[PDB]
Image: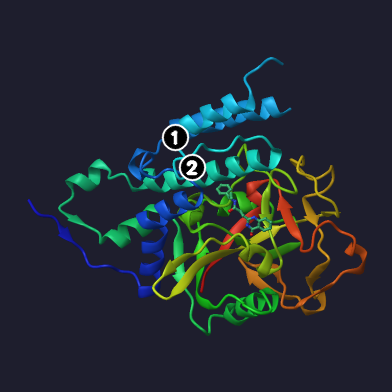
Amino acid sequence: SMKRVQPCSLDPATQKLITNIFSKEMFKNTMALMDLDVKKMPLGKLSKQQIARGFEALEALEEALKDGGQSLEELSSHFYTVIPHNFGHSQPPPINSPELLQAKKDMLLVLADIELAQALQAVSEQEKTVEEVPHPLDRDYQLLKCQLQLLDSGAPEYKVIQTYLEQTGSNHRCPTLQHIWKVNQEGEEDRFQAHSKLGNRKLLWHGTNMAVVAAILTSGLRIMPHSGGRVGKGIYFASENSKSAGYVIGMKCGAHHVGYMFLGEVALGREHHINTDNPSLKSPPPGFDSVIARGHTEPDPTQDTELELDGQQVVVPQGQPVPCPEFSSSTFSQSEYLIYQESQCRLRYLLEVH
Ligand SMILES: CC[C@H](NC(=O)CCc1nc2ccccc2c(=O)[nH]1)c1ccccc1
């Protein structure tokens, strides 16, 4: 007979976050923004197998791009059969450049995290048998297996975070800070403790699609087989909020535009600095723990402060960006900070920005 729904334990801010990051509208919006045909690929129909077939088709395309084999056209057509796209019921375009191939890999990585959020929400048999259920938002929070604590104005780190955001965000249209949560994804702790000898820790921005926030809270920042970009197959961070905010896909809610950004503690250790793009990188050179694509600018190092997190000092930039004359000819306007092991980052904060 009828189960009791227990009252929600969550504060309003956290309720809104959990509503947003599991929202079916949000997920379908994201799919439409990536040109996917949501009518032929509904959320409940997404499968790991379908996604795996999509990567196989792109793998075949990539081989063709590097025979008497199938044309890029034919191979593209196969991809589009496996992963339905919407282009106003015109033909979808051929995947015939490295840039576009990577764009499709990135779409599929986002889609794989949407599928993860759907799988996560599957109702277990224990939940079918208990006579009282948590409020749906408590249930969704619990699935993350990630502790979130909303911070108020006088948490020790609050002003330091706000200063990082303000001093390194866009000069004309800085994102407006609404909330900060401390993030404790346990199961990150053990692997991150591995690098406690490794110095040079920095708190760095990671901006993303709203649609991958649940996945990240569940599994941490990840390097996937088809990950790539201007500095290769790693996890990308920025020291300038404005660089990371470029990757934030927010969603219109009422009269404003809501977005989420992370701050991670990154054990950078011995840095290798580059000044030109290298998409082929899969690790730092021998003897180095990270790769920094150095920008024309950097938050003024003289203003760096520190936080203490789990008894370690973590550098937090507090300065506006200034020119770095040694990197004035860099192919990078702003720095990209790369690690190539998922263990070298721990999620620390999540921010809601408008
Ligand atoms: C679009 C694919 C997506 N990656 C991201 O959301 C990271 C985006 C991002 N890139 C950066 C690049 C340089 C500097 C900073 C950033 C950043 O803050 N976010 C992704 C989603 C799921 C699984 C792996 C990767």
Q: Nearer the viewer, residue 334 or 137?
A: 334
**Could one spot residue 194 in this view of the protein?**
no
**Sequence-first tag of 2 and 1:** 1
For label 2, count other residues whose C-alpha is less than 10 Å away and answer few (under 14), some (14-19) or many (20+): many
Where is mark 1, residue-wise?
A: 48
Label count reads 2
Q: Position of residue 352 (x, y in %)?
A: 50, 70
Q: Quadrant of residue 193?
A: bottom right
Q: Quadrant of residue 158?
A: bottom right
Numbered disc 2: secondary structure: helix
Which residue corresponds to the image point at 66% horizontal and 30% vertical from the top-left?
Answer: 62
Q: Amino acid at mark 2?
A: Ala
Q: Nearer the viewer, residue 289 or 322?
A: 322
- The reply, left or right, for residue 181 in relation to residue 196 is left
- The reply, left or right, for residue 220 in relation to residue 121 is right
Q: Nearer the viewer, residue 234 or 243?
A: 243
Task: Pick out the residue farthest to the top.
Answer: 68
For label 1, count other residues whose C-alpha is less than 10 Å away and answer few (under 14), some (14-19) or many (20+): few
Which residue corresponds to the image point at 27% horizontal and 59% vertical from the top-left?
Answer: 136
User: Tags 2 and 1 in contact by the CB under 8 Å rule?
Assistant: yes
Task: Pick out the residue farthest to the right.
Answer: 326
Which residue corresponds to the image point at 73% horizontal and 44% vertical from the top-left?
Answer: 232
Numbered disc 1: secondary structure: helix
Tag of residue 19: none
- Label 2 residue near ligand 1, CB within 8 Å: yes
Q: Cα distance, mark 2 to mark 1?
A: 7 Å
**Could one spot residue 284 in this view of the protein?**
yes
Where is mark 2, residue-wise?
A: 112
Q: Position of residue 311 (x, y in %)?
A: 64, 67
Q: Position of residue 219 (x, y in %)?
A: 51, 49
Which residue corresponds to the image point at 53% horizontal and 31% vertical from the top-left?
Answer: 79
